[PDB]
Length: 69
Image (tube, rainbow, N blue to C red; front, side, top):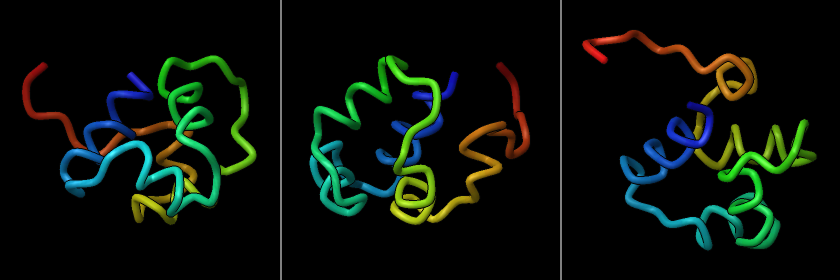
């Protein structure tokens, strides 16, 4: 799912939702809202994309290979 990508990448980055929120320049609450999927388009698209170091296109689509499941 969407949040799985963000969160999984967060885990791989070894960072948490609050750190990500600060790196994005928002509040953990906003991140958690995005994670549970209670928004349609995040204002912080570029900020999230940069925070993880992926493309907005991948934030929207979110496809980088598939090795089982």
